[PDB]
Amino acid sequence: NINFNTKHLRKGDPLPPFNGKLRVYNMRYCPYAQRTILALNAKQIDYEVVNIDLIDKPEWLTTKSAFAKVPAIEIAEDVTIYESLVTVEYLDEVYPKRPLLPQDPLKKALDKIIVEASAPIQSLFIKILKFSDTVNEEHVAAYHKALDFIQEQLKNRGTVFLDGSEPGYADYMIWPWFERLRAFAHDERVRLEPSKYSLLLEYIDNMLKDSAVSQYLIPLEILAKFHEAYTKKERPNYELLN
Ligand SMILES: N[C@@H](CCC(=O)N[C@@H](CS)C(=O)NCC(=O)O)C(=O)O
Ligand SMILES: [K+]
Ligand SMILES: [K+]
Ligand SMILES: [K+]
Image 1 (cartoon, rainbow, N blue to C red):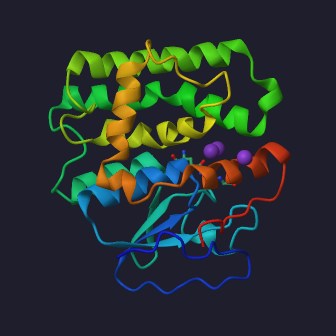
Image 2 (cartoon, rainbow, N blue to C red; image 1 turned 60 degrees about the vertical axis):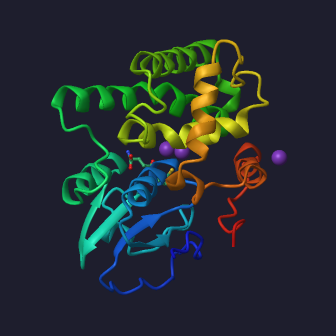
């Protein structure tokens, strides 16, 4: 029912009036904002998306998102939450069905640790994307430590997904970087050796089939095109899907 690909709004664009639907201030290619989409999808919460041009930001953005970042959710008129993990934790507390976070505090903590474990991945991706020349071997090594740790958590838990037979917070909150890893899979510093990472590669295949993931997937040729702008220092085209 939801259109993920309405125009990204720029300075001079009007602010659509609140209409009752929970609203996400998003940008289609933002992995951080993707966390909020995944959560909303998995929990089957009705919502609407307002896309934001991050190069030429709407004047009224900081009104909704103090740090001028995405995502932000608006849960009522002029009442907003931002910071991706903050938004997801709010939705999990207020919408009880399909709980993303473990109820047991210890298990909850482990999930958050796992998410933190993906920082080196988040880091390598943004470096390769925007500061590619500065990418050294500590970055690449840290990234591999990151993958090792995550795979091992999955191995130890023995389940299909980090959070069980259905993906949960840990899965969804790291997923966007795995979605992106797929498009970096022919840069040599990212490609995964299939013996070492066969369990992780299998998990990624299964994630692609989760309906919260699949309905929001970016076709890989589109994502590569998008990334291309950055590596050339071009002005982003936010409308490739529209
Ligand atoms: N810690 C924040 C970070 C989110 C973030 O970095 N959003 C980026 C987009 S990928 C952004 O809005 N950058 C604003 C800019 O272009 O200055 C979160 O988890 O929500
Ligand atoms: K980014
Ligand atoms: K960033
Ligand atoms: K390309």
